[PDB]
Image (tube, coloured by chain):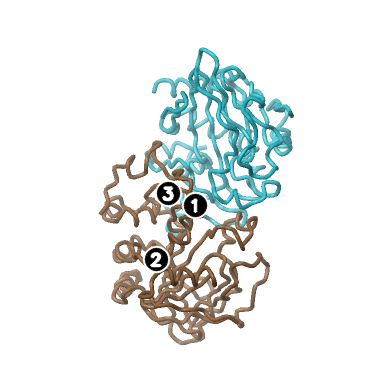
Chain colours: A cyan, B brown
């Protein structure tokens, strides 16, 4: 049973990406200031449930720090561009979600996320493009006992299967506020059972190539809030054109670039 | 060289669908009334260029008959649901475009449209899901000499290739105002040479599974126009949630159906 491997963010995004290529998962330690997560955690806190797990989206409206600091985190965009740029091109958010795993929440059947898109089932996982990257920021401490994400490392190249592993056999992502788990959509994984007394809160961001439809649309966000954000974070939440590896533009408006057609102001 | 096969719409959409799965292309005759196409042609004219070929989008804005009669054409949707429902689930428009091919427009190198999405290069064409369906309505007569679409029938199951055919070797889609050419994104095809002296206008809808990002976004179509459209036409233009074959919703607002979270009225 391989371990979940780790690197400090000070060691560089390429180290984290090498482990992500070899294992399909990596824990990056100290990748974002804990105060950033603390603000975000208040925004979320001062505000939809299955298997004792509370899901909450709309983070663009809920939190200015998410909108500004998290969506722009350079380490994450370096790793993401390593993953998507040559095979797929521009990436953007599939969704961003808080997951509040209450006590009594039960571990899920280990699975691949990229099952969500049906094409993944007609491509060879050994040689196919990655369709999803997931970045999870603990909002409180992640341990095995409180349901920290279970991962089968090095499971990202084998064929699609109807069974991968029993959740009891798997290691847990154990990490602190300020760290992040990154796993690809071909990594076998699942939430763990929160067998503790306190909730286990994490902030999962799922990014995908720009040619795949986001699960969560941000068409309801006021343009005034969106002109607050950088061009990159606008693109992340779907307010921008996305180009494929072949420079083919999708999400264009009136034959022009999205920002150009709308006259959308940015920041930075 | 196989011929482009033809059926009349009165023969039903399963007839056309069977020809489309055997051949990757079918011409459906008399599928839509030519007065409908005539109203669309006026609406597009009142709006008055590579390879001498003029492209025009924003048909949702420029034409009410498009928004209403064309995007709801039941024959097209019966075919599109035969192509997409079991393998992919909900479909919606990749784009809707008007193509005015002027005298002097030269024929394109034949190609597969599905190349636009890179995953198409990692799936086996013989067994992979269709990523794209194209429906072309002539706005005036399509002949071989004025650039009628060139198609290589039964080319839809072979491997992705850097070469498929020379345009000179391909038959043309010939059809009147009121017919429609349907072909998948694995059919090898290209625009032909317009060696006539009048232009050749056609209206190409491209549809795809709802999990693939439309090339044309419709987010600055006025809500009040969108609320005059059917729920289906609204979904087609991206103002709707799309669900895959596993009933997972994409394009949702606030963990709810797009229409629910917007309070979007329909017709």
Quadrant assignment, res A158: top right
Q: Earlier in the sequence, mark 2 or mark 1?
A: 2
Q: Earlier in the sequence, mark 3 or mark 2?
A: 2
- Pick the front one: B213 or B53: B213
- Pick the front one: A113 or B163: A113
How would you rate the neighbour count of disc 2 (Cα within 10 Å): few for under 14, some for 14-19, many for 20 or more? some
Q: Secondary structure at mark 2?
A: helix
Please name the residue shown 54% across and 37% down the image: A206
Q: Kindly identify which residue carries mark 1.
A: B213
How would you rate the neighbour count of disc 3 (Cα within 10 Å): few for under 14, some for 14-19, many for 20 or more? many
Label count reads 3
What is the CA distance from the residue labelled 2 to the residue labelled 1?
Answer: 21 Å
Residue B261 image point, x, y percent: 34, 39
What is the CA distance from the residue labelled 1 to the residue labelled 3?
Answer: 11 Å
Q: Secondary structure at mark 3?
A: strand
Decide if residue A224 is in sight here. Answer: no
């Amino acid at each position: 049973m391989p371990p979940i491997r780790r690197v400090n963010a000070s060691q560089g995004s390429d180290a984290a990406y090498q482990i992500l290529q070899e294992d399909g998962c990596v824990i990056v330690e100290q990748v974002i200031c804990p105060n950033i997560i603390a603000k975000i955690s208040d925004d979320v806190n001062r505000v939809n449930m299955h298997n004792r797990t509370i899901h909450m989206g709309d983070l663009v409206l809920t939190s200015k720090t998410y909108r500004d600091e998290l969506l722009n985190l350079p380490f994450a965009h370096e790793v993401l561009e390593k993953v998507f740029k040559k095979d797929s091109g521009d990436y953007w958010l599939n969704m961003g979600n808080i997951l509040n795993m209450l006590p009594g929440a039960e571990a899920q059947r280990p699975h691949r996320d990229d099952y969500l898109y049906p094409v993944s089932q007609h491509m060879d996982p050994a040689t196919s493009p990655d369709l999803m990257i997931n970045i999870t920021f603990p909002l409180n401490e992640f341990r095995h006992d409180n349901g920290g994400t279970l991962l089968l490392p090095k499971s990202h190249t084998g064929p699609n299967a109807d069974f991968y592993a029993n959740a009891e056999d798997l290691p847990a992502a154990e990490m602190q506020v300020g760290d992040a788990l990154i796993f690809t959509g071909k990594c076998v994984h699942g939430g763990g059972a929160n067998r503790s007394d306190k909730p286990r809160i994490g902030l999962a961001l799922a990014a995908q190539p720009g040619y795949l439809t986001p699960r969560e649309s941000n068409v309801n966000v006021p343009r005034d809030i969106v002109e607050t954000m950088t061009p990159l974070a606008q693109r992340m939440i779907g307010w921008g054109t996305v180009r494929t590896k072949d420079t083919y533009g999708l999400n264009m408006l009136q034959d022009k670039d999205f920002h150009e057609a709308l006259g959308l102001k940015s920041k930075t």
